[PDB]
Structure formats: C-alpha cells, structure tokens
Amino acid sequence: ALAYPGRAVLPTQTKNAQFLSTAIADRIGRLDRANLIGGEVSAMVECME
Amino acid sequence: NLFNVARGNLYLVQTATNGNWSPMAPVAAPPFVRGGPNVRVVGRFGTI
C-alpha cells in the first residue's frame, strides 16, 4: 500500500486524501511487459510505482 | 433468479409500512432513476 499511493482506500477528506483523490487510475502497476519466449520468464517489464 | 442471482441495481429507501411487500418484484415505481432530477453520483472513493 506504501508503494502504490493511487491504490489507497480514502475514508474521510483528509489533507492527504484531497491530493490522493486526484490520482489517475491507470498510472499503477505494470504497463507493457515484453516477454519473448512463451512460457519462459520475461525480459523486462515497464512498470509505474 | 432460479440460480439465486438477481439482476438490476438495488434501492435502499426507508419505507415504513404495514401493507404488502415484495422486494423482488416491486409493483410501485422506482424511487429515482440513475440520471434523474436532483440525484447525485457519489465520487470514486466514497469520501465523506
């Protein structure tokens, strides 16, 4: 929960929460993993965190 | 509905009554529609 600030449950309008409420919801997690061989481990994965 | 799955959104109005009640098939009109007058969709986080 500490590496993904856009993923937090926001209860009341805290001074944190009025900034986290402006977090865009697709700027989280992996983006486009570029694996070659199907079944083997991937090459490099672009992620936002 | 045979498989214990109901469709459609769920209202939660407080309706104190003594009469007939059937929440599955309401004969009366819906309390309001999703985009009606003086209705408001709550944000994204549910933040009070």
Image (tube, helix red, strand yellow):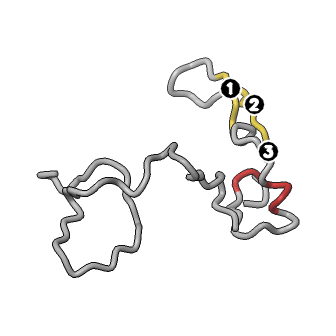
User: Mark 3 touching mark 1, by CB under 8 A?
Assistant: no
Tell me if residue B24 comes above or below residue A25 in the rendering.
below
| Percent coordinates x, y for residue A43 in the rendering | 69, 26
Find the distance from the CA under tag 3 to the CA under tag 2. 10 Å
**Chain name for mark 1:** A
Q: What type is the residue that disc 2 sits on?
A: Glu
Find the distance from the CA under tag 3 to the CA under tag 1. 14 Å
User: Mark 3 touching mark 2, by CB under 8 A?
Assistant: no
**Which residue is at a point 77% across and 53% down the rendered structure image?**
A21
Same chain letter for marks 1 and 2: yes
Q: Secondary structure at mark 2?
A: strand
Closer to the camera in the image, A9 or A4: A9
Dot 1 alpha-carbon crowd within 10 angstroms: few under 14, some 14 to 19, many 20 or more: few
The label number, if any, that marks residue A46 in the structure image:
2
Dot 3 alpha-carbon crowd within 10 angstroms: few under 14, some 14 to 19, many 20 or more: few
**Which residue is at a point 19% across and 56% down the rendered structure image?**
B25
Query: Which residue lies under the disc numbered 1?
Result: A32
**Chain name for mark 2:** A
Among the 4 quarters of the image, the one containing residue B4: bottom left
**Chain name for mark 3:** A
Q: Secondary structure at mark 1?
A: strand
The label number, if any, that marks residue A21 in the structure image:
none
Q: What type is the residue that disc 3 sits on?
A: Glu
User: Mark 1 touching mark 2, by CB under 8 A?
Assistant: yes
| Percent coordinates x, y for residue B5 in the rendering | 23, 53
